[PDB]
Image 1 (cartoon, rainbow, N blue to C red):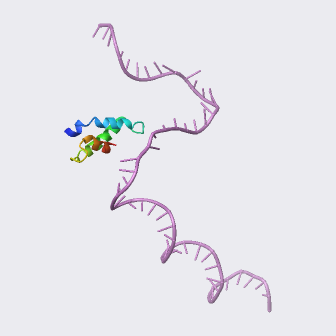
Image 2 (tube, rainbow, N blue to C red; image 1 turned 60 degrees about the vertical axis):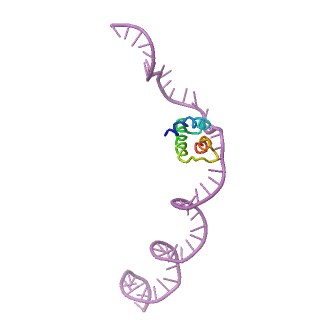
Length: 60
DNA sequence: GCATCCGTGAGTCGAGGGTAATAAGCAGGGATTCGCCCGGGTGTCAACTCTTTTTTT
C-alpha cells in the first residue's frame, strides 16, 4: 500500500494523454490505479531498476 | 433581525434536413460459428378393391 501510494501521481501523467475517447478523467485515473496496483506485485531487481519503467507498461 | 446567495418562469401553430473527431502488439488456452451430410418425418403420386344411383335392359 505504501509503494502504490508513493507512485500514485505517476498514473496521472499517463492518463492525461488519453482523453476525450469516451471515458471520463476519474474513470481513467481509477483504471490506471488498478493497473499500477496489479503491476506492483511483480517487481524484482531486473535490468529496469526504476519502478516507473515497469509500471508505465502496465498503466498504459 | 437583516445581509448574502441559489432554485423557477419566459406563447403558439407552422417550416427544415442530413451530420461530425483518437487509433500498440503478440502468445497461450477456450467458446462460437459456418459447411456437408445422413436422415426421419411431411408431401405428391402410380395403382389395387367395396357402394350404389341410376342409367341402361
